[PDB]
Image 1 (spheres, helix red, strand yellow):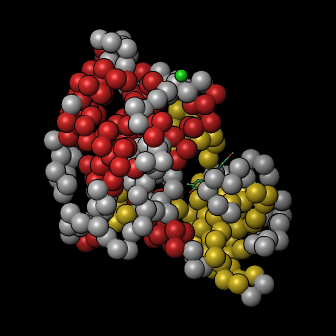
Image 2 (tube, rainbow, N blue to C red):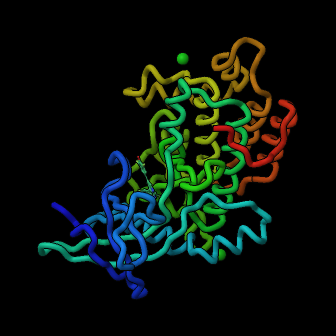
Image 3 (spheres, rainbow, N blue to C red):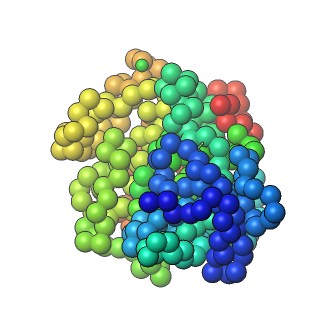
Length: 322
Ligand SMILES: Nc1ncc(-c2cc(F)c(O)c(F)c2)cc1-c1cc(F)c(O)c(F)c1
Ligand SMILES: [Cl-]
Ligand SMILES: [Cl-]
């Protein structure tokens, strides 16, 4: 069922007018089309926006839209960038949304920034490795993103390379996308209790998800940092220890628990003997110390990663080296 007539003009709830172009990408993030401001011109291949469209009863797009409306208003992000002295913040900007009826069905749409490639494609093209420099630079910016969304009451729960997109015009700026299964862990400053949430079905992506998620409890801040930990190892080494048994969640959980209890054994497993990046172990030890409701010391985690850059003779110059 086609959701749009190509070239049609759609008007959002703020009465801003947009024009719809052709589909973009290999289907990973649902029904998405290139989009631009309304004009006499057709929407081109270099369009600065995309429009996401789903049935109005689609739960994930409603969840995602609420996240973007609450936490990703352009001015709200810019104010944080200024006050925290960032070069940029990799939370996509929300440009508008509305309702669209076609063929007796109701759809919701949302206009967002258009991005370039996802990191998973680039990773695979680099024979499933990123350099230590790249991993550290990615992770510093992901820590900025996680701090910002956690301070706005949300956790992501599904950090991974396929959910990391580059700025279309700047390949040193990485953005975290896909908030359809994001979780509001602290609505109005009240932290969710250590417990399953019946409203949440999602467990994350099995190879990267947190021990909390494996235990059936709602995701919290420590879980997001743990996920990033597993991503860093995957990116550095091409592997995780539990990757041959991902059809058995009990196995995956058991391995993660054992490797949290003995982080030195994780470093021995994942890295060549005596050749483990010390910042990765220190990062994991720091995350291990977090309680379920505890606010992370994000600057301490970034300082740990910055020691890694110093150790390889570099600095945080914002260069992803992709
Ligand atoms: N804004 C975007 N721009 C380009 C792509 C894209 C995807 C591909 F899979 C691909 O191959 C490609 F070239 C481009 C995806 C998004 C996008 C961003 C989000 F934040 C989402 O939540 C989302 F669903 C989609
Ligand atoms: Cl705010
Ligand atoms: Cl390999």
